[PDB]
Length: 427
Length: 134
Length: 12
Image (cartoon, chains in turn cyan, green, orange):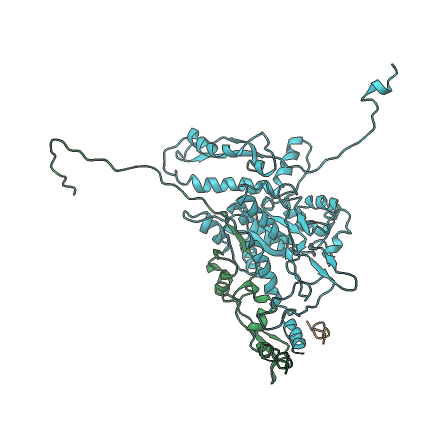
C-alpha cells in the first residue's frame, strides 16, 4: 500500500507546472546533442524570451548596439581568434502577434549579418486554431494569408532578413508517459518502483518543436557530406529515423499514437511551403517523418519574366542560403590571413575561386550523398578594384545551386497513333 | 653571439632555418541554441545579459547542466511524513535523468522515507521462515 | 489560475 502513496506523491510533482517546464526545456536540448559528430560543436545560451523581446524591441533601429548581436557577431564572428556561429536554433514558438513579429525581425537582422540561418517553430495560435491537429481542416493556407488578419505578417515576409528565418510546423513527442507495461520507470536495485503509472489521455503530455530535428539534420548534413543539400526529401536529407511514439490500452488492444502532432497530407506539404513554413510531415504508422520543404519565410513572388520568377524561388529556399552563407564564413575568416599581403584583382579571383572550384560540377554522381558533396552548379567571381582607396576592393559572386526536385504533373493517354502499323489504314 | 666567431679558412655552417606560412586548423560548425532553460535559475542566467558566457557542451548535456546550479524550491501537495507544511521539492539537477519519476524519490527527502521502508519492510523473509521443513 | 483540475483530478 506504500506504492499507493508514491503513485500519488511523485505523480503530484511530475504533473506540476514549472517542474515539467524544465523537462520540456531540457529534453529537447538532449535531443539535439544526441548525435555527437566529428566536427560539430553545439553551444547553449539560456535566455528568457522576454529578455530578448526587450532587447530587439529597444534596439530594432540600432541593432549594432543590441546585446545579443554583441554575443554572436562582434564577439566570435567578427573578432580574430573567435569561432563563428552557424545556424541559430530558436527553441521558442512564435505567434502572429505584432510583438513576436519583431522578435524575428531582430533575430533575422542579426542572422542576416552574422550569416547564421535562424530556425524556429510557430505556435498553433498562428492559424487561429486552438488545436494544431485541426489545421488539417483548412483547405489551402494560400487563401488563408489573404485574410487581413495576416497583414502585419505579409509585410515581414517581404523583408530581406526573412530569407534567413525558417519556421517549422508540427511538434514531435519527446517523452512517452509512464506506464508499467509501457515505458516503465527504471526503479532501483531494491526499491520497487517500476509499478508506477502516470495520468494522460487525449493530447497533453509533453511536446517539442520540429525545429530540433531540422537543425539536428543540418548537423548530420555536415559530418557526412559537407554542405546543406542533405536536409530535404526522403531519399536525400530529412528522414528522421526512429521517433518516440506512444501506445495505450484504453479498452481495445494497445492503440498506437502517432509520434507527430499533426498528420499532414500531401497537398499540406506544399500548401505550407508557399506560406514560408517548414512542415514536419509524418508517415502514418511508420513512426517516422521527413522534411519535404525547407523554405524560409521570404515571399516567393511570381513575376512575368521567367528568370526573375526562378530567382525568387531559389532565394526563398532555405537550404541554399545555408550554403551561400558558408561562403561568407570562408571570406570573412580565411582571406583575413592575407590582409597585408600584396595582392591584385587577378590574385583574389584566384584564391577565392581555386577553393570553391572543388565544390562545383555538372555531372551527377550515383546516390544522393555522393553527389551532395557538390552543392553548387557553377560560379562567377568578378572582383575589381575601386578608385580612391588603393588597397581596397569590391567582389561580387553569383552562385547557381543544384536545383532540387519539387514536383511534377503528368498526363497519361492512350494515343493509338504511336504505332500506326497496327491502327493505320494501309494493311 | 652577435659578435660572431672569427672566420677560419673553411667555415661550414649548416642552415636550419625554414620560412613558410603557418597552417590553420578547421572550424567546427558551431550551433547556437537559444531557449529559456533555467527559467531564471542558473549562475549564468542570474547575471545580466551584457555578460552571459555561452556554454559549449564539450562533454554532454549531463555535465554542462550540472555546471549550472539549476535548483528549484516549488511547493507541492504532501502525502508523506507528519506535521503540516506542504512538501517542498528542493534539489539541484545533475543529469538529465533527474526528471525521471525515480531519481525524484531518491532526491526529495520526504518521499525517500517511504522508499526506505520498501527496502526493509518488503525484504521480510516470510519465505525463508515460512519454508521451515522440519 | 484556480487549479480546479489538479485538485478535481484526485485519482485515489
